Amino acid sequence: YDSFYLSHFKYFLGPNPYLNTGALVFDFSISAPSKVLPLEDYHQEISQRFPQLESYPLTSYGELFAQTVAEVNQLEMDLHLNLYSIKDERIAVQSLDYQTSIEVVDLVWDWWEAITKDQRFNYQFRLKKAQETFRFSPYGGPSSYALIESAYKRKIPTFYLPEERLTQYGYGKYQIRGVSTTFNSDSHVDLDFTTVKDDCKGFLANCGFPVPQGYVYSLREALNSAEDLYPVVVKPVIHKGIGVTANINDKELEFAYDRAVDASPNQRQIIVEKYIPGADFRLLCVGGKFVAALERRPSYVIGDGRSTIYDLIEDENESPARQDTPTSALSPILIDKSLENYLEQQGLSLDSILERDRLVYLRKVANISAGGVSINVTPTIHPDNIILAEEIAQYFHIVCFGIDVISTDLSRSWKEGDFGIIEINAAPGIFMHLKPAIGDSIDVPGKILDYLFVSESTSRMPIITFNYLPKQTLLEIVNLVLQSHPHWTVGSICQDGMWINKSPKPLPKDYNTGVLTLLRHPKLDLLIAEYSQDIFETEGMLYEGSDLIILDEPTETEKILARDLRKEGILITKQENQVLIQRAE
Image 1 (cartoon, rainbow, N blue to C red):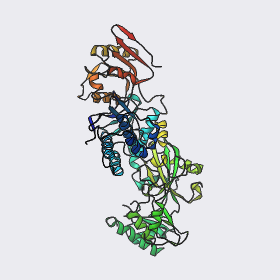
Image 2: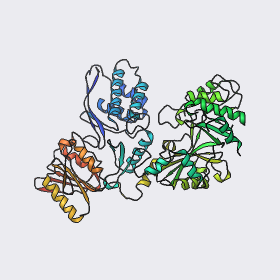
Image 3: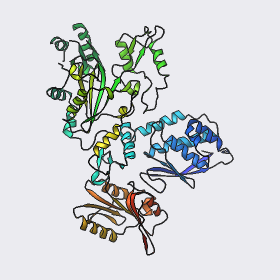
Image 4: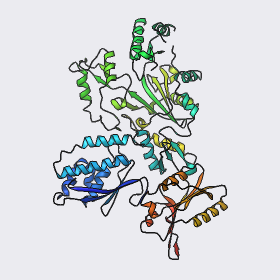
């Protein structure tokens, strides 16, 4: 690091003096002014990678750096992190994860050293590293991320509860907590039950649902399944298509039994079911109501009499539709054990030429992340299939509920017969519904939040903040509030201690842990909290904005608190003996 230099790094979870949200903050400077002579050349190489920057004015080295980092922070997942603040060469960039954000800044720093010196910067490698780091942050998983992005645009506060490993949505008594598509209202019993395939299938069958019928330790038992009142499916109890043979007479079945057993020998514990032809569809209900349906089509190649499967896969992977980005709608076809096994089962291999117009599926079970195709088929679903989904969902107190079915045509009513329910997913992913390879997206994250907060006009209780709040003042205010609202829970925190309705509680060493405790309180009607400069510049603010802000002889840093004032909030300021009210708007 000879050309440019970064120092004085600070990370804030929430709003701080530089940004109104969480951020990584650092000081930008130049070590070698004689080497970093161009500004335009940095602009050009960077804008070539990020052409949207050609719309920006070229000002300082610091601002260009900040912009570069802000763009890089999006990685390739369009994360809503393209936000920066620069003043006096101090750069703040929006940050979801401390470790990830540092990696990004180092990436850009090393990149600029390379731009200055010998170029040849391995951007892809460094980015992939950052992407992987991000993936193990609490927001790394795209179904969790989508909910955050949605909560942001919906103005529902979110923060992370590290002892619970949950995201909290909303404040105080309005709170929802959750992990991904699973939430704290979801019933333990009801969830547990969906992990038991046999009892779950039995129960659904008894409710008149189209559950496939089935009967195995020995091949003799496998045979009995097919014999007693038909083509079958053979899978071991223990999966994901491993050892799976389907559309099976006696000889085919002896073979299929062996397949399942050899694949999983410790589970010799074999499942033999009547075969249902058709595509694999996911039916999703949210809040008990159907929201989306999606087909998961295995990837495939078409013959030509000229070229091998390997060649056909490579040609298909040149399609611009195939992207490596973890959150692409469609991955390049990847070659793994599952693909090779499925070809073997067809008497095919990679080095095999297919006849003109022959279609060959590469996997039995689509893996979207490895090249399968996600199709939004919602607009064509038969109303009876919508109803089926809802009639199943109504029995489980689970906010997000997925049903995996097989059908030859989802536009035909299940009553027609080429239809059956294979699996229940009590905490389904939703990303693929937001980003299908084919068809319109469905804002499922949106629908989830809409349902969760359907009953309330707000996701958050009122917050009062002060730059200075001595115990005396705090308690007088608490007293008045309770006189008007004696049934309320009022959480109050300042440097002098913390109280709930007059009852003192120990103050944690981390100020914001105390604040967290209050936000997390399920009955909280009102939060009152101090953020003196000592804290604002050290831990930062934990919640996103106040309804009432009070500045008693504030420092210039303390005055910044005023930025995060809710629409129609009030800013009270005291200087000498005068007090201003200033309704926000």
